[PDB]
Length: 53
Ligand SMILES: [Fe+3]
Image (cartoon, rainbow, N blue to C red; front, top):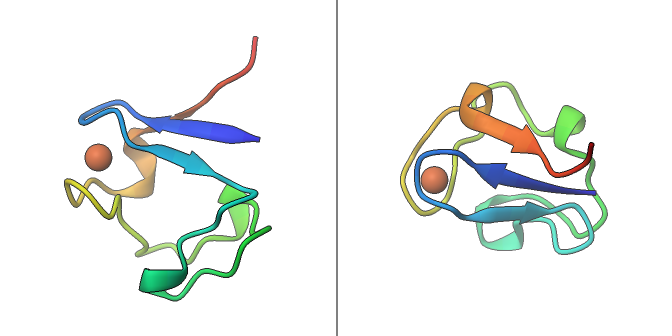
């Protein structure tokens, strides 16, 4: 799945992960640590929205 940072438009792509910040490719958004933040703008996980109907 992909999720959008509602602040800055960064896409958390579960297939890409976030390896520069400790997240291997394939990590579901729910499994990101509670204090993981958007790597672009610093927004908390609460500011992301899943890109699905
Ligand atoms: Fe952001």
